[PDB]
Every structure is written in structure tokens, then in C-alpha cells.
Image (cartoon, coloured by chain):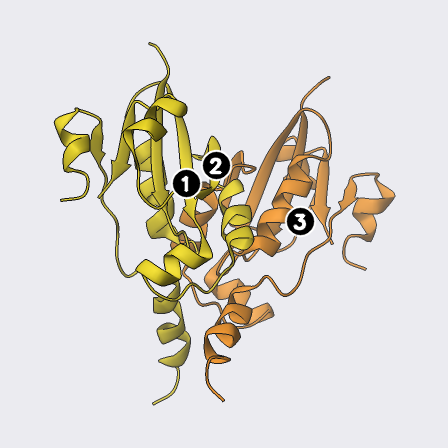
Chain colours: A orange, B yellow
Amino acid sequence: SKNVVIYADGVYDMLHLGHMKQLEQAKKLFENTTLIVGVTSDNETKLFKGQVVQTLEERTETLKHIRWVDEIISPCPWVVTPEFLEKYKIDYVAHDDIYAWLKRAGKFKATQRTEGVSTTDLIVRILKNYE
Amino acid sequence: SKNVVIYADGVYDMLHLGHMKQLEQAKKLFENTTLIVGVTSDNETKLFKGQVVQTLEERTETLKHIRWVDEIISPCPWVVTPEFLEKYKIDYVAHDDIYAWLKRAGKFKATQRTEGVSTTDLIVRILKNYE
């Protein structure tokens, strides 16, 4: 089977099991894949999304340790373009409208997340040790 | 080069960059390695060490996503024995006295940790947004 290039992007702030399973899912979309992960910049995240706890460098260094991640684009563009797909020979974008053009092209693969496994939820747990 | 079996054990509660780099270091002790990671049980951790935020299942499921981890023993024995090394064909124990017999046998490889990269330190950071 030829090698399929998959691109997933995100903030990956305080990486948890939810992110990890999402990356695993992207990586296992096809038998033979290269999973490329894009990591959004601090400024663009803050402008468009919200506060980020970890720097770009911290968020990227953590992702490097994840089994499913084959390549990292850091920082990545905030918006995926057709030129970007051509530049990196990407076959599919994996994510969970703005991806409408990707779907029309047949280049979108949906991926889900899991809840209750997040970093902020662990603090509640430490806290729930006190009435 | 023959394949060297490395064993590292730990709690791996709320896995962070510090743990990840330690595993990477164990995994790269030799050119060709199998890194086996042992994950301590909830009861024994609590008895001998302190509180654990995440269950054995949660701590093991996270470790599964780490690139450097080749095999997981979960739960693992709290104390490493010579019989345990023989059972799993282990060549070296990688850790940071109680490992004295391991050193005498030539079966101990030291590994370090990093600080300021921990999960609890990230909460200070979110908090330090308020006087």
C-alpha cells in the first residue's frame, strides 16, 4: 500500500489522553501513513481561540514524544490552504463550515475526541479531596 | 548489535515532559533496545509513596501513547528482584541504597529527570494570572 500523508493541526496545550487518542486515530486512518502534526503559534492561538498555558516550544517538545507523530510543522499556519496541501504533499486533513472545501475535494477525514480525560479535570480530582 | 532489554519502573502519575525525557533516555541507552516500563499499582503507591491522582488504568493508557515505550508491565512489582530480571530477560534497570545489588551486578543504568516541566507547575502558571 502506498504511504498516505495525513495532516492534523491544533493547539495541543497541556496534552492529555484526549489529544493522544485523536492523534492515534489520525495515524491509523490507513495501513501505511505519515502523520504530520501542525502546532499553532502562541499569538494566533491567543488572538483567535483563547489563552494558552504552554509556549509553542513546550507544546511542540511534548508532541515529539508521542508515538503516532511522524513529523511536526511548528508553528503551523492557522488556516489550511490548497497551496499548503500541495507544498507538503498532504493527502488528507484529519480533524473533528471551514473544512467544507476539504470535504468537496475528498481530502477530509473526521476524527473525534474524548472528554473527562483532560488536564483541567485532574485538578478537580485533587481538589475534590476537600469539602 | 544485539537487542538490549531495558526496564524502567515508576508511578507515571500525570505524565509530563520530565517523565517523557527520562523514558527517552532509557530507550536510547544503547543503539538497539527494548524498553519495558513497569507501572506501580494504586495500593502500593499509596502505601509507600503518597497520593496518586490517576488510576493504574489511566496511567498505563497514557504511557501506551509514548514513542519510547516498547512494552508495559502493569501493574509491576514494587521491588525489583533478580528473579524478575530473569523472568523478563532484562539486561539493565534504568532509574535515578536500594539499587546497590543492581550496580554490583552491572545491571544498573542511571537516568536523570528535569524540573519545572511538571503538571503541578502548569497550574501555578494559570494561577499567576491573578495577584
Residue on which the image places disc 3: A80
Badge 2 and badge 1 both on one subunit = yes
Residue on which the image places disc 1: B38
Would you call the spot at circle 1 few (<14 residues within 10 Å), some (14-19), or many (20 or more)?
many
Q: Chain of mark 1?
A: B
Q: Chain of mark 2?
A: B
Q: Nearer the viewer, residue A93 or B100?
A: B100
Q: Position of residue A33 (x, y in %)?
A: 65, 28
- Outermost residue, right direction? A104
The kind of residue tagged 3 is: Val
For numbered disc 1, what is the local secondary structure?
Answer: strand
Taking the spot 50% from the left edge, 89% from the top edge, the residue there is A131
- Compared with A127, B37 (above or below) is above
In front: mark 2 or mark 3? 2
Q: Nearer the viewer, residue B80 or B107?
A: B80
Taking the spot 33% from the left edge, 43% from the top edge, the residue there is B21
Q: Chain of mark 3?
A: A
Drawn side of residue A103 relative to residue B71, left or right: right
Spatial CA distance of label 2 from label 1 is 6 Å
N-term-proximal mark, 2 vs 1 = 1
Asked whether the beta carbons under mark 2 and mark 3 sit within 8 Å of each other, the answer is: no
Q: Position of residue A125 (x, y in %)?
A: 51, 73
Would you call the spot at circle 3 few (<14 residues within 10 Å), some (14-19), or many (20 or more)?
some
Residue on which the image places disc 2: B72
Spatial CA distance of label 2 from label 3 is 38 Å
Residue B117 in view, yes or no:
no
Drawn side of residue B15 relative to residue A112, left or right: left
